[PDB]
Length: 461
Length: 133
RNA sequence: UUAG
RNA sequence: UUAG
Ligand SMILES: Cc1cc2nc3c(=O)[nH]c(=O)nc-3n(C[C@H](O)[C@H](O)[C@H](O)COP(=O)(O)OP(=O)(O)OC[C@H]3O[C@@H](n4cnc5c(N)ncnc54)[C@H](O)[C@@H]3O)c2cc1C
Image 1 (cartoon, chains in turn cyan, orange, green, blue):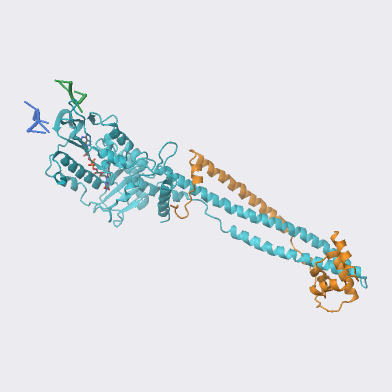
Image 2: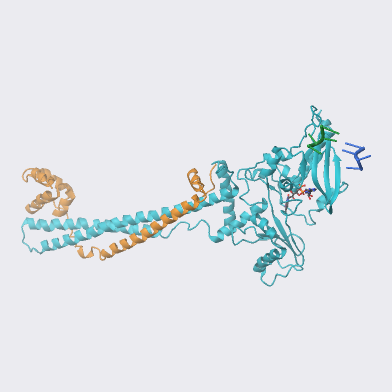
């Protein structure tokens, strides 16, 4: 609770840093959420030290008050030692004595009395300062901003945030990464207990779908389009699909691929390509662990694992169990997701069991039956997981992604009113990116725009 | 429009930490040094103060005297008149002091005495000689 | 090559 | 699909 609270407080701090101090540029480069977070954290460590220093500086000021006092009390103890002796000597002059001698006794007496209670006033002040010092020395301020154990648990909340955005926090745009928070849906988050694929399969019913057909080139012209595709099972076999319009649903990762996996003819305009470069395409992976026995708490839908280091904070930081079956589903996020793809399944499953043995006991963890490891960045039909608002980008790039292309005329001096190349998919919808419902809505949008443009919109008259 | 509670972010400090790649590290170890400079200063003064307190051991108890009580009296004896004139020569116009010497004359009677014995005791030129010290 |  |  303590760290999750500080985590949320640190995020608020970055927002303040962004909106109130215009800390959105630095060295002619945009600031990332990661940069701002380190800055905030560094200033929290600076403040902890500024308070420590202020506290010790009040002690010395108090101690130097005491030293000046003790010095006066010593030089006063001596004046009193001397005046006492002078008084005794004057008192030893036995009476009867003349009045100059009686005066001396009386005079030195109150001189001695005057000083004897200056010393008492000071010894009073002494006790005060000494006590004021035991208080300070008893109430030191905070020692560190974060213990090594704190940072580690904080890194887990960062990993969970890197997981949600499918990217390292150093890639996210400080200004814009949270633009679509306002459009969040109400209600509790849910999962599909019979598999999310039941949806696309259901949608596929009644449609003409050519599977194992990899588009290689998209030609869009004043007179129509032709799409060149090959059989993925034998890439020599070629097909030419001719049409009035093309709806491009290719993932942003594919569109980013250099050299191109899909060539556009003529080449896409710079305002389109520039947007494709600026937008981020993140990555995140999962490990499926199939056992014959449940050895975990079935009532717990999910539990975490804190990384030893900041670097490995995304490495298998979270585990799912939300299916009536002996399956654990481990999550890999942030910088880990990318690096873990260059690691064999054996090693990966190994680290999973290691972590689990350390939590449920080195004996209660059997070797799994089935295992599966996603590698979405390596998947050539995806080249990543989903889009994120990269530093240097904005919400407007999502709109540019959605703008259709109108090729110029073939015949010199002819009019070219209609478009031919349309774009949909998760990366094309400004208010609901990186989601299934966002992909869904992008589809409905272009279907309506294409129909508006080719069938005509009668409802606007 | 304000940082979260207990969160500290000034225009001044952000520009300092972001001045470069190690501007952060620099600032934080300058304070680590200043934190050491003062920590040992305190250890030093603790030792110095410990020593001084050691000297005052016993304090002034061996120098305290019974404070004899005697209550005021209206009449001025020749003895008391003479104590007063001397008290004036030494203390100037500290009436409280002069009263503490004589022992049985209130602070007011001292000022009365100043006026009453105006010239019989040449009180003015006595005070002059005091101011000359 | 948005073949002319 | 020698797209209609
Ligand atoms: C690990 C992971 C977890 C996710 N979890 C969630 C979640 O919990 N909640 C949520 O709302 N969203 C989640 N998403 C996002 C969601 O899955 C996607 O945003 C959505 O499914 C994308 O729909 P799309 O049609 O835009 O893209 P796609 O589903 O990728 O459709 C593009 C199609 O084009 C194919 N293709 C690619 N290249 C070619 C080519 N040359 N020729 C022909 N076909 C090609 C691809 O194979 C693919 O079938 C997750 C994504 C990933 C990667």
